[PDB]
Image (cartoon, rainbow over the protein chains, first blue to last red):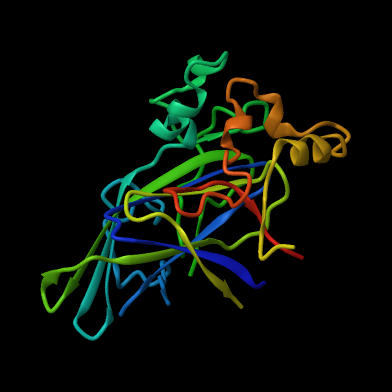
Length: 33
Length: 210
């Protein structure tokens, strides 16, 4: 329940791909400086 | 780190018949004073349709398995294979609400300050947990992925074929996902075995801690 978080700066396109016997899910957010 | 409330329909527009996401569907919200982000779905296809996949599988016995017209599907040899799965959706977390699917989604990302375009910084994470062969990949077209901590050796560990071969010999009946030899699941693994692809544009499948 502590999940690893990665970031990309300067993206205008961003993708998420899943293949699983079960189910996965996506959280997405922004950093504002 | 402002996470996106994909449930807040007041910020969403152009949702599909099932209230989920389709191409053209848009999330738009003032995330902080002056600052507006706009996420628009540009694509709903799985990983085996990507250039990234294409380059990985190219010039190897599984090149022919690149399929640019693949759609979001049930895994072959599962009880609903050929039935069209449900729309992806929020209604704090986006998820395709049904088991045994090879899917994917792309978003256009835009951001404004006081009405002027600006360079957005985006963070991503898998909400669910994953064992081997439960594959979760993140792609970007911006700067390479950096780890920024966690949200409550390892902090995470990278999924491998040695790691998947095992777990396969455990499900007893065999792992469903791997039966389907029409897709090279070996190539869903990140080739960056050290980290899972930091410094790069694709943060290939990890496994979350205990």
